Image (cartoon, rainbow, N blue to C red; front, side):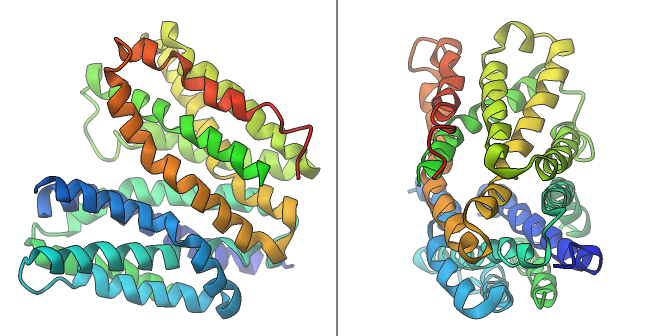
Length: 355
């Protein structure tokens, strides 16, 4: 366990992989809305988003029996074909298959393997390393739209589709390198509502923030620092009591989601956003270290796969829930007063029975 050092190569590989994957996933927004029953577009987008997590449990066996490297390069090749293919005509079913199925399965193959073998070489500063990887992913992703838009040179749809395969090619070159889950999914149920709330509140009355180097950075600045410091704190805390980290994160996240009185004012809004980004880091990133401490390196792959599979459905359900409840219970304020109730539920049994 060289605990980093020469393993900073591994960390850089993880940063590039996990950043680019979700960068192109977010770019799907540009894809299906500008480069694309018209609702088939939304259905295909939802299918693509789900396929990422859905097949991760199956990807787990591939990873275990082939080494992270083989699965990573295979998924890289699949995606490389994917976002370049559909070079045929705009046929409905042809495009559907080519983009959706291939992109989803390849991304599901390529995402998970970046989170298995790291522990075998990282033992003492693994939490800090995970925080660093999360920060790198955040910074790379938030600029990913800027980079693609800038060096895309305003080229047509097909050529842009083909170009976006360059990141996957570079990834392929770089690729040579239950109660717990129930509660964590319960937390995920409420995780995403405050994200939409903050984004819309920032955009509404503070439209002067428009630049890609600023707007997405408005949340990224908190995201990276919070993720890194949370990883360091987790590496500091010994044992499974780290669970208390996400316990506190759930409490604070619910409180902030409830903090309507002060979210409406910019002065308190800045601090609330910083806290929410801290909590995002505490929640999203701590999962892998917690699973490692819970089950050991041998089972980490299956554990993370199972957790991601469970989280899949709530993740896709989030934005639909927000949209439906925006006007369901009179007003969204009352409809989402309870936004912290789900994490409150998740913050109950996490001491009586850890496993």
